[PDB]
Amino acid sequence: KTYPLAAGALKKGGYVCINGRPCKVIDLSVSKTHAKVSIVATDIFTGNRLEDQAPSTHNVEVPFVKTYTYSVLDIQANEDPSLPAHLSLMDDEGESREDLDMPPDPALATQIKEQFDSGKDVLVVVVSAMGTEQVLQTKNAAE
Image (cartoon, rainbow, N blue to C red; front, side):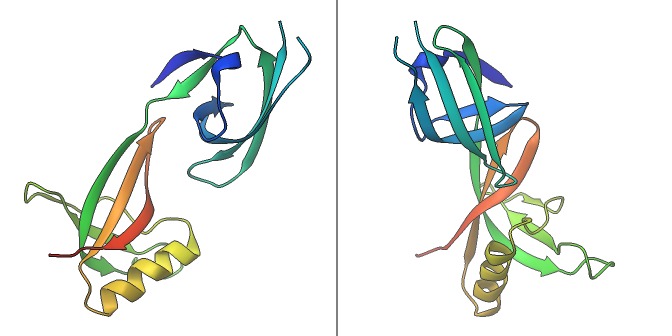
């Protein structure tokens, strides 16, 4: 879920929820002084730009954000070729999961597939917040 933070304590780069969505602050401004804090933030999952403003003493909600890194065991197209491919992913204890798909970020999905087809050990960083889980980054493993 979320935890409270005084809006006057928010910093650029910090997480914040706006309209129930988990975002990273990309711009902040404060009125002359208390003060009003104006926020512009990017949804970490959809990439949408969201804005909000609050008194510096109002508590904004900050999402709990969790990250986990998996390796890619397989990529399989959806029975409906127009939808994202399915991923088979291995965790660091030898358990796999098959419930996650390629992310809704075409360039990132392409990168994961190209690296996998080149015979790399492809890692995906899965981030979870506000009930959503999505691959947000990829990189290749080394020995």
